Amino acid sequence: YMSRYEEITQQLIFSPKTWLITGVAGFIGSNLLEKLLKLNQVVIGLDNFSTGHQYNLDEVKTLVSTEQWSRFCFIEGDIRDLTTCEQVMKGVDHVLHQAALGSVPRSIVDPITTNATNITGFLNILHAAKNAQVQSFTYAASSSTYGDHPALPKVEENIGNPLSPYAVTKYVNEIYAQVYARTYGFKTIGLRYFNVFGRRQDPNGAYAAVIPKWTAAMLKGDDVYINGDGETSRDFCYIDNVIQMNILSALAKDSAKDNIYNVAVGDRTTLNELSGYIYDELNLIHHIKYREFRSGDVRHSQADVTKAIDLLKYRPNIKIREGLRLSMPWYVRFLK
Amino acid sequence: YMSRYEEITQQLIFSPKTWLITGVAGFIGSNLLEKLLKLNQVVIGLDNFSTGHQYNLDEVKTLVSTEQWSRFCFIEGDIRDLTTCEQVMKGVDHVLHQAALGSVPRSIVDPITTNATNITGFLNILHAAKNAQVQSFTYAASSSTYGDHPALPKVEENIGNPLSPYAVTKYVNEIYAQVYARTYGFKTIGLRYFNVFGRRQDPNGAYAAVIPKWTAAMLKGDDVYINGDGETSRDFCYIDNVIQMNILSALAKDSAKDNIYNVAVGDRTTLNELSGYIYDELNLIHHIKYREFRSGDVRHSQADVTKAIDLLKYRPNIKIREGLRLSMPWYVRFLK
Ligand SMILES: NC(=O)c1ccc[n+]([C@@H]2O[C@H](COP(=O)([O-])OP(=O)(O)OC[C@H]3O[C@@H](n4cnc5c(N)ncnc54)[C@H](O)[C@@H]3O)[C@@H](O)[C@H]2O)c1
Ligand SMILES: NC(=O)c1ccc[n+]([C@@H]2O[C@H](COP(=O)([O-])OP(=O)(O)OC[C@H]3O[C@@H](n4cnc5c(N)ncnc54)[C@H](O)[C@@H]3O)[C@@H](O)[C@H]2O)c1
């Protein structure tokens, strides 16, 4: 039971608010959109369809009622444009900022566009939000920000040197957010996501994340690569845990704001064990080679989620194996 | 004797190199331009005249020969435009990046503009320099990167939380520089300036620094305002000391790069002390109210310059009073 999250969602349905979701056409944004519309929220979406897709928005349309869909106002535009950011902020209560160009290797190969998207765009949205006096502001940060810190499991206060331009940009979001609290009284929540997965995570394209990239490949009958020795290990976090955490963050009591939280389940899986869970869930619905470590990649990864548990009453309820089970039917349909 | 510095400057007279100075029309930039043309160097300059001034360049022109000035190629443009950054990098040996919007309070009022210039702009010059494979890259960092850290004197490896949007931007310059070393092998030097003063520092405008602002006010018979009880203290650093450090860093051995250095004297002077020094020096060349502490003002600032002295062979040989003596005639001339 996700007790606190149930209670908060009940408040929202009784007293609905206006939400802004940036990155709404993407993986996490469109999952947020689906749950907020199902709570009868008014939703303002912004996306530029860089890595996001209109098909994600069309899919969410078919999953909600007509009245629910009628409260979604979609704005095609770019967070790099401050005017656009101010326009979409108007009358907004709760900001969920997901728009960014993700991926460590992308940042290495084009630190420039990435900087513009992830620092300039973040600041534009942060500043428009402060000026519009929104009730809350929650933004996607990253476990990449732990960098080379050798400690396991990862604890929020203890971070290392950032190991790529992507790590830098996300860390910069966090420091601007803190400076905003201290200089303006504008209290935010940053969510360090660990390896999120689930429906509508893009499997196509050179930057695909390991779960949908492998899922696709096994469905193709293609080779399943493994960047390095395979002992690299991760806290894979099903999207529903992330949706819980965004919504708990948006309605957090004030003293839980101006804080960073790990967003994950606290477990660890190696590239090598995941391969098998994926085969088994897929193989259940009727259907491997080693190589060089990837550049600027974090070696080993497990979150300590004690802080979200205690301060927000986060209750992660969906673990790697069940998330895969829940996720595979989506991949079959999308790829068939 | 500034002796490694003398050896380096003698060598440059004998073997000119091509330098890029961004912010060339500003206080520190035009002073670098002056030194470099007098050393017969080839200098590419870049400035948008946002806080810099064409009269600064006209002044440098009157101080160097026709043949020296003919080695100055000046481009009016903006570091926020990557193309411009690439163009001015061509043929460049040594980068001295000074272009930025200074001032903590400017950044509080308009964090967006300060971000675009200080982070986007800085990243464009760093990236173009890396791509051009220049010999050296040195950038203007800031003592505001110490933030709330309580150590005093300030030592480079120990820093705190940044306290304004400005401080965020200058800290991010350092982080990007370190990440560029790590990921592309491009090793830079960051110079944490402390309260620099001297000729061509702008006395006009909401954000003038204390030394020129007071100097101008005494020359006009305007009220000199002390923000607080005047026991507040700084490590005021004459320009020539900064010129020295820039040149020592452009020519540093490889082991001294990918390092941050404080640039200052090592001394502390109170606002009360300073107001007396300024008066004394001016009135030798011939011619006060207390109010509220500036809000969110640092109380005491003093640099440990051990690292610069040991690793770069820096000599902080101009202290505050001699610096004021050297600067006062330029203000007298400038304002009469
Ligand atoms: N999925 C994970 O494992 C993970 C891990 C760490 C951090 N994150 C962060 O989570 C957020 C959501 O990521 P996601 O996995 O859903 O990726 P995604 O690529 O699916 O979503 C990003 C969305 O933002 C939009 N966007 C990008 N730049 C934009 C711009 N300039 N203006 C407007 N829209 C823009 C894209 O079109 C896309 O719809 C991002 O900030 C990402 O950095 C995700
Ligand atoms: N003066 C100090 O005590 C001090 C203290 C800490 C750091 N610094 C840093 O030293 C550097 C030089 O500062 P300064 O005191 O000479 O200030 P300044 O304002 O006199 O000089 C900065 C120059 O940069 C130019 N510039 C700004 N934005 C630009 C852009 N986008 N494109 C092209 N040109 C641009 C301005 O027009 C100006 O000529 C800056 O990086 C400043 O932050 C100075």
Image (cartoon, coloured by chain):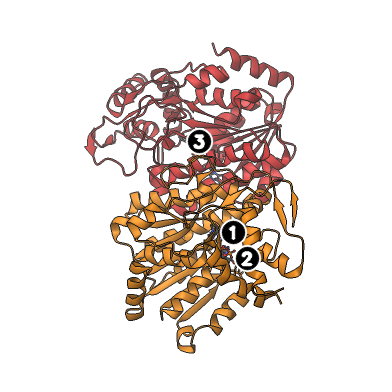
Chain colours: A red, B orange
Q: Quadrant of residue A204?
A: top left
Q: Is residue A109 visible?
A: no
Residue visible at 72% across and 73% down? Answer: B287
Q: Chain of mark 3?
A: A
Helix, strand or loop for disc 2? loop
Q: Is residue A19 visible?
A: yes
Sort mark 1 into few (<14), some (14-19) or many (20+) by Cα contacts within 10 Å: some
Pinpoint residue A216: horizontal percent, then vertical percent.
37, 33
Are the residues tagged 1 and 2 within 8 Å (C-beta)?
A: yes
Nearer to me, B119 or A95: B119
Pinpoint residue B212: horizontal percent, then vertical percent.
64, 65
Q: Quadrant of residue A58?
A: top right
Point out which mark residue B51 bears: 2
Sort mark 3 into few (<14), some (14-19) or many (20+) by Cα contacts within 10 Å: many
Q: Quadrant of residue A196?
A: top left
Q: CA distance from mark 3 to mark 1?
A: 27 Å
Point out which mark residue B101 bears: 1
For residue A48, above or below residue A144: below
Nearer to me, B284 or A310: B284
Pinpoint residue B87: horizontal percent, then vertical percent.
46, 71
User: Is the residue marked 2 within 8 Å of ligand 2, measured from its CB?
Assistant: yes
Q: Earlier in the sequence, mark 1 or mark 2?
A: 2
Query: Callout 2, which amino acid?
Result: Thr
User: Is the residue marked 3 within 8 Å of ligand 1, measured from its CB?
Assistant: yes
